Each structure stands twice: as structure tokens, then as C-alpha cells.
Image (cartoon, rainbow, N blue to C red):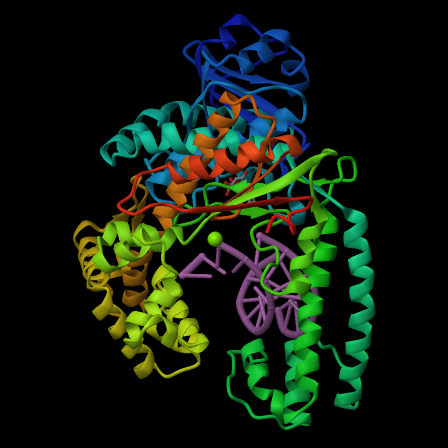
Amino acid sequence: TAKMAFTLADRVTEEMLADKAALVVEVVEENYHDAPIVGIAVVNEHGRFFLRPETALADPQFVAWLGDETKKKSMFDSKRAAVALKWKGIELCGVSFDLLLAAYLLDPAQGVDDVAAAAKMKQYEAVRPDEAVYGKGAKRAVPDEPVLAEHLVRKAAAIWALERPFLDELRRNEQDRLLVELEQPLSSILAEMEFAGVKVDTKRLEQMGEELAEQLRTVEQRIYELAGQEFNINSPKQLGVILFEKLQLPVLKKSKTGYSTSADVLEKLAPYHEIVENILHYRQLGKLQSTYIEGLLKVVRPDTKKVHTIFNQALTQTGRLSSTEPNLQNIPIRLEEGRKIRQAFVPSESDWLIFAADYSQIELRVLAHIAEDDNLMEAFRRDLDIHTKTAMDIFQVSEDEVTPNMRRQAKAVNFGIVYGISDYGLAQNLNISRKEAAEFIERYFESFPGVKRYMENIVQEAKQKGYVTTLLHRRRYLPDITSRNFNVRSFAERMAMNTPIQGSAADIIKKAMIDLNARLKEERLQARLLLQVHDELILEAPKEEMERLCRLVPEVMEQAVTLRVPLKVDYHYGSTWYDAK
DNA sequence: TGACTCTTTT
DNA sequence: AAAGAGTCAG
Ligand SMILES: OC[C@H]1O[C@@](CO)(O[C@H]2O[C@H](CO)[C@@H](O)[C@H](O)[C@H]2O)[C@@H](O)[C@@H]1O
Ligand SMILES: [Mg+2]
């Protein structure tokens, strides 16, 4: 392939500082926090340019251009560059188009994760995949300057050529505003959150780990006694031999590889031998120790004593965020021993507090809205306990006739409706038969005929159109909706049902984040957004701001969109994330 | 290195 | 429904 033409500049010139350009600020490290920038490419009306970062980032004019909002840039994964630049004390402004976010909105199923993959969607192939240039795994490395510069320039040239086709298709999809007014402003907001980080009380985590280590050694030794020998408890294969061969415990569930030792299998095995509950206890403690004490500690920055997560804004099929290093969206809450981990997440400044606000049943409320189910809407308009009310309806009983087991099962039905699990999935969850599960679902549709109507209609719409959409026009293609394989087709149907629910909830929280950031600034508060956990926002703020935030945050969240039923937000604050409960 | 298995969250 | 730790082939 002949090299694409470009100037390998030694110095920044005026013609590199046009008010419209494709810009590449290359951070090759997967985790971009305080990570090197290996090179820079600019493409504009005047030409193609490669700049060495030590030159560019020391040039007052270039830096000024980077921070000038009126100088428009087109990029791929602008958040990566923005954050890497934040660590160097440089502001990136004026990013008017992000090809990563554009490709993501166009079809999240494509898994677009480099410029090449995005370009391929429009039959543009004059750019290499990053993996071919940098290698992968242990072989991963930055190549020599000629190879590096050409690659960065080809990526920039691709972005420059692809902006128009991508924007055009977004417009046809009615997704132009979704990109420009939602995902892109959110991206700046996430960059600030990641950069700010969350303070961690490492000392408390460490002493927790010490306590766990003691309890782990105790249970582990007890396990060896009950087995009559030592083995690797964390090896499902070895444990399977102890349980199902040495101890002759029944085999209720198997895997592709051998015996299942899932927690739900073990729970059923407990009455047979004393070893089982000890194994369950071991795995609980071991999960906390390895994943949440040791894992968290590994990624706390020693300089700051903070964790700086990375939100992947371009991954999920539903439009949710995910987060990594650490993942702050699965910190334990359910069981008290796990929940205590949240005590280690503290405010980053003295006399500040953690403030958390969460939507109450936002997914079921969205469902009531999109389905226009009279019963479901009435229930939310009365702010009823939705699980108790669902139990009342399914079992045809009065509120005081609802037993705890009845409510538990109604709750599992709702969870099934919300996440679109199979009737086989409901059966598994409630430990009942499919016939019984199917009866539950059938009773539900009798009490909520509008939801049944919605399930039917959306599946048909997915068939006819080839995709489903959310409130704010996020899209998900479902080509498997026509499949002749039952399991493949059924999963697609469930995704047709679930996506406008989970996706629209994602849309709403994302808008609330944008609305909140603007309100905080207007109100001149020092409060800052730290985390989003699917349906909740977590902030830290001076204690003197708590009373104002108690009024402000739920109002912004509740008013983010207007639905046929109210949105409800609960809130708490305290000296640690644990206490904000 | 990657397929597997298991566990945590919403 | 949909990140990461550990094990065990290759
Ligand atoms: O920068 C986040 C952004 O990068 C992508 C690849 O383009 O993911 C990379 O970065 C993530 C966080 O460090 C990694 O988890 C991921 O494995 C890595 O490829 C995008 O998927 C993401 O939106
Ligand atoms: Mg909640």
C-alpha cells in the first residue's frame, strides 16, 4: 500500500489550527488514566499532519486550539483523549463529532472498537485495525515513528471522510440529536467523573482483608476435615470429585465439562453433608477477599488513594454504561458482610459527604408508560408497593392476605418482566416447573392486559421493522426474530420486549446526568458527580450542601422526562457510601 | 492464551 | 439479562 501523504511536522503551524479538523490524540494503553500520549494527527482543509506530543502539547497555540470550543474537532473515543489530557493539565474542547459514539448508536451489535471497524460499516478500508498495528497481548507495542505516524494520519483521514455519511444515517434514523445532545455531552460528563475518581479508605479495606483471611483459614481447614483430605476448593473439578465421588452426594445438575457446583446446586445438597454449607461460606468469603478487597486495592492509585474507573459508553446493547478497573457497578449490597465494603468509599475532602439518589422502579414505570397499561399506571399513580400489588392481582387476594412468599414470587415475575428472562428462566429462579411458571405469567397478563398487548405488539414491530427503539430513539436490530430455531427466536423476542424498557431507562438517567451537571453549575454548588450505577447517581459534596441537594437532585432526576406516570427518586447521604443508605 | 465456571450488581 | 477471579487445558 502506498503511504498516504502527510507532513511529519517538527513544529506547530497556523494551518494546523483551522476551526474544523479530524483530530487523533493517541493513547495506546488500555487504561488511559495518567497514560502516555504517543502521537497526534490532524487532518483539515489544509492537509494532513503528524505532530510529536512532546512538541504539540508544549506549544501554547496548539494547547489554546485544543481548549477553544469554537474550533471544532472530529474524533474517535474523545473521552480517552480528554481524560489523558486532563492528567496533563490540558482541556479538550469543541469535539462536535465522535465516530465511536456515532457507530455505537447506528448499531451497538457491531462491537465497533476502533476506527477501522467503524470505517468498514461504510465500505471504507484505507485504515488498519489498531490490533494489526500495535499487536495484541504480550506482543503489544508502539511501532516505529514512520509506521505510527502513518496509522494515526489514516485514522484521522478516515474520521474526516466518515463524518458526513455517519451523520446522514443518524439523521435518517432520527438519532442525530441523540448523538449531539445526549451521548456527546454525556461523554464530557463521564470524563470529569473518571478524572475526579472516588476516594478509598485503603486502611479499612486492608483490615477487612485481614479479618477475611482469618475466617478463610478457619473455614478452609474445616473443609479439609470434613473431606478427610486437602484439595483445591477453588477448582470446581476437584471439589466435584470430593462431593460427587468421595462423598457420593447426588448429581442434580451437570455442566459441559462435568459436575455443576453452582451455589444453587450446593444449597440443595446441604442436608446431605456438613461440608456443603462450609463450601458455600468459603466461596462467599473468597469472593469478597479476591474480587473486592484484593481486587479493589490493586486498582487504587497510591498517589491519590482514589479509584478512577473507566465507563464504557459504547458497549451494551441496551444503552447502559459498563465500568471497569474497578467495576463500580457490582459492589456488594445484598448481604451485610459484603455491603460493608462500601464503607471504604469515602468523600475526597474533609467535611464532605457522599450523596446517592436512585430511581424507584424506573423500569416498571417506563413499562407502564410505553404499554399504557391502565392497572400498572394506576398502581404507580398511587405510588403503591408494586410487588405487593402484583401479588394481590395474580393471587386475587387483599393486601393483608399477601404472605411473604407470595410477594417474593410476584417480585420474581416483575424482575422477569423487567429483564426479559424466559419462562424457563422464571421457573429456574422460583425453583418451580415451567407449567407453573407459565401459569404465573398467564395470570400476570390477565391482570395487566396492556403489558401483554405491548409484548405482542413490540415483537411484531421488531419483525416488521427489523429493530426496536427506546424513548430517545436508541436502536437495537434483532435479525434473529425470524429464526426457525426456537431458542434463538425466543431470545430475540425477549430482547424486543426488554430493550425499550431497559434502554429507555438508560436514556432517562443519561439525560438526568446532563440536566444535573448543568443545574449544579447554575446553582454554583461544589457538589460533584462521582458514579452512575444504572438507576442511581452518586455524588460527594460539602456537608453544607446536603439540604439543598436533597431538594435539587431528586427534582432534576424526576423531571428528566415526562411520562404518563410519575418518576420517583429516593435519596440518602452519609460519611461513606455504605451510610448513604 | 483462551474456554470454562462461578459470583456480584441492576 | 448481561466485569472479573480462578483453574486447566492447549
Ligand atoms: O476507551 C474506552 C473505549 O475503548 C474501547 C476500545 O475502543 O475499549 C477499550 O477500553 C476499555 C477500557 O479501558 C477496555 O475495557 C476495552 O477492552 C478496550 O478495548 C471501547 O470499547 C470503549 O468504549
Ligand atoms: Mg433502586
